[PDB]
Length: 152
Length: 158
Image (tube, rainbow over all chains, first blue to last red; front, top):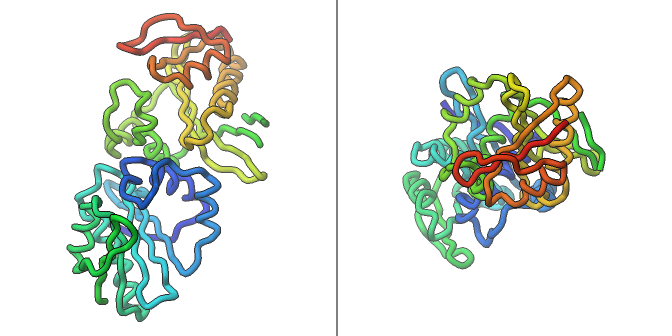
């Protein structure tokens, strides 16, 4: 079973360690190095019009932090959805999909009509994930980046 | 145990730290330095390690900066049932490397070992791990003996 809960201060280091793994930041726009704390903290301080959750996976009477899911641009009619699962061997097990659908349901219920994701051309798993939820490539983003959109 | 330099503190690990610890060890930039690891860890392997622990202590390394503390690595001693326990160290944040955090953390562990009556300690280090070699030699460790392939034991008298 999957549950998502809001991020706290305490999760900052775990979030950074996921984002500092090259196996993962190969999929983030222009990131070439692991994160520095001041950049990570500065991101944390400058958060506006967004919600960030930690993904919790329950199995065998254990509950663990497995990734993060977020929406930003909530001051628009088309908020942006981000999804990161930190455990590399959980990929392909629909944890990302289920987590995004939790945020999509929330978005729909609070009145948003659309939502989108920015994805790099090489990020095939993310593409499959969003397309399994009905998103479609509608627009080019920055270089080698594409915007996928859904109707809620 | 704590170590002003900003300040380094070490505190015992907890169930809650497990995912962060796995996240550091699953980074290829780190596991480059680990005997034969070629892949990120799986939770089942990581958690089976955790439920298997004996004759060891693991700490999280805390860095206090602007008077606010954060988790930056892990330091550990194992083989405590012998007269020559093994010390392991890992700094998870990458742009902290080369700032003596690992050195100070290890020396905190050496002081704790000494005070309860150990007289020796060692580290197992891969040949390619130049920062770790410098760390332990800065504390007086001496290359002593081959470990497994491309791996060396470095020992110190406490």
